[PDB]
Image (cartoon, rainbow over all chains, first blue to last red; front, side, top):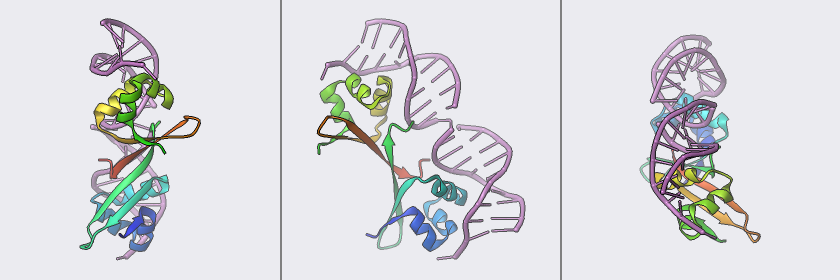
Length: 60
Length: 60
DNA sequence: TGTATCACCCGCGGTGATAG
DNA sequence: TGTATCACCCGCGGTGATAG
């Protein structure tokens, strides 16, 4: 609430802001996205963001 | 259904079987567990297992 | 239907192993 | 409220940078 996708979020906001919102470098995002990582953002009232990723175990 | 925790599963079954069930080496498990990784198994009728892990983005 | 190291290599997450 | 490389280091996931 709102639960939204990284990619998604990225298309709305632009790699940079996003990236900035997670306190990480833009290239990350990019990579991450192209990467096809399953990740989700969570927005809070204030607009702070939280992101978790889903991955299969085991990583290999 | 059933949704169960790795650790959990591990306590019921013993590191080894588990490990075997995921097609990975026992030490992994161990590590993984001690590691405090958030991971979950999913059991199916037949008893096949599937495991996904939850992680914060970004990994760093 | 034991677990917990250990060093090795592509620093996490694995591998094999070795023991117990 | 541009994105997409690139080489570098602790092979994935990041960093900075460089450009466009």
